[PDB]
Image (tube, rainbow, N blue to C red; front, side):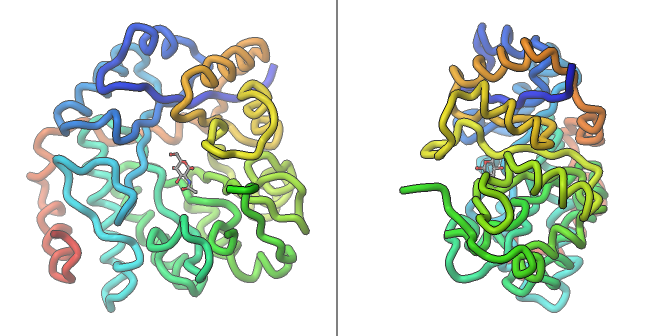
Length: 330
Ligand SMILES: CC(=O)N[C@@H]1[C@@H](O)[C@H](O)[C@@H](CO)O[C@H]1O
């Protein structure tokens, strides 16, 4: 008897026979979509509606930030990279309009959540963060990200920060490492997570090892999650996990043990993406563990609804005009 949940994905654009069957299990708590699942706004809207007909309580998420990481394209406005938002005097509200406009549009197609914003610091070396972050100096990036979260919450969408405790300095031979003292990490990459700890609804851990703190990745470290995230930072939200079926991950064992290690470390929901066979393995482990969904998991449901006329409300006009006034909307 413990707590935990599973977030998986599908293959095509509509639900297959086994997709409907595997979704009916209560241990499955979420579903995340990628480019292979998206075609049109009216299509992804019906895709969510098809899922709610099966599980009205399921969590539907997607990777929708600004810049190169935007899965919703064919019918959606192209949002600029969050680094481009910083280079403006009115950048605080400019990021606030960006969070509101991103959440309202992805909620208009039936989705609950977007894994945004990135809280990583744009130092020189990490390439996977790059333009996805705001700036390199810490305290300003946390100010701009907090404004981005204000816009998301204004649209009724919960925000999830990525990637705890920091992916900006961690540079396929092994999983990247960040060999810096905890006192040195807290002075740099950790403070954006500290400032926004009480504001964020959820967090995703980085697939990074910090040797002077814990010998494991953050997504499995009881010390990173239970000792300093919940105790020191006083984060009372949802702890997602890294991709437990990550391509090229250096975690020996099957998905059944990867999800058990994450739940024991403090994670509430486990992600298995682009690997169906691993989703059944982790589902089978959660069933034999007899887990129930954590009470925090419902705070992630999007307070918006699938709306065809979301372009009618006034703020959509003011936000759209304010963003292209700074040359951000194409
Ligand atoms: C380091 C990185 O890019 N992390 C991504 C995260 O942004 C995304 O939300 C998640 C689910 O697709 O998968 C992770 O691997």
